[PDB]
Length: 9
Length: 227
Image 1 (tube, rainbow over the protein chains, first blue to last red):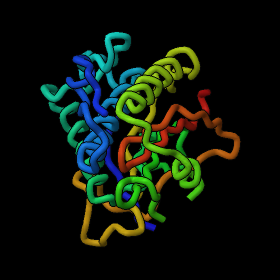
Image 2 (spheres, each protein chain N blue to C red; image 1 turned 45 degrees about the vertical axis):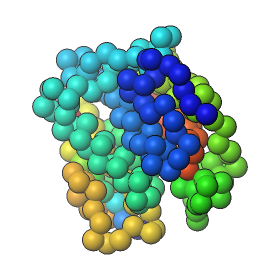
Image 3 (cartoon, chains in turn orange, green; image 1 turned 60 degrees about the vertical axis):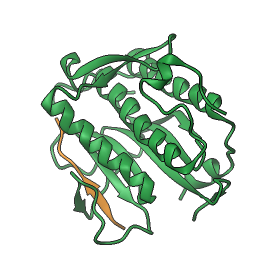
Image 4 (tube, helix red, strand yellow; image 1 turned 120 degrees about the vertical axis):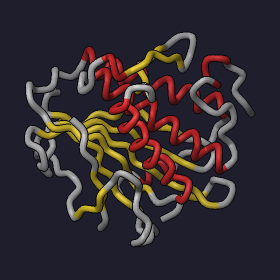
C-alpha cells in the first residue's frame, strides 16, 4: 500500500 | 546467552535476546550486509568502504562514515534500520535498474522483516511470513553463525555466481512500510511512493540467508537477470 524510495548511483 | 568474541563486539551487540538489542542487531546487520552487497557487486568503488572483521575468519568492506557520500548511504540504512524499533518496516531492498526511475529491476537484493510479540515467540500478522514465523530464537552464538553465513553467501554469490552488472545502471534503496505504520511516520531519506519494484517473469531467485535474534526475523533474497 505504502512505499518509500531513495537516490543512489 | 552472550557472544564472547572480540571481532564480533566491534560491529555487533554481544547480546541480542532483549527487544532493544535485537532491533539494534537488525540495524547493524542491515548496515553490514548491504555494505557487503554494495562493494562486492562493484556498485561503489573500494574507496567508499573500510575493511572490517565480523569474525577472525571472515572480512568484509563496510561503508566509511568519513567519506561523505558513503556517510549519506550509511545514514539512509541507519534510518531504515531504526524503523525496526517501532516495527514499521516490512522490507528494505537494494534495487538496480537500467534507467533511472524504472519500476522493473534487473537486480534486487531484498531484506524482509518479521516482528514477534511479547517475549519474541509469536509472529505479528505475505509469502515470506510463514517461513520466518516457523523459526525459534536459539541464542546469540547461533545468530553469529547466521550472520557469518549471510556475509559469506553474499561474497560468494557476487564474485563466483553472478555476472558483472551492465555498463550503465541506476541503483537505489526502496522500502515498504508495515500495515501498522502511521501515515505521518516517514523514514528519513525516503520519499513516499505509489510504486515499489517489479521483476521480469523469468528472473532468477536465490536465498542468501536469514537472521533470528530475540524478537525479530529477517530474510535476505537475491533476484537477478545477470545470474
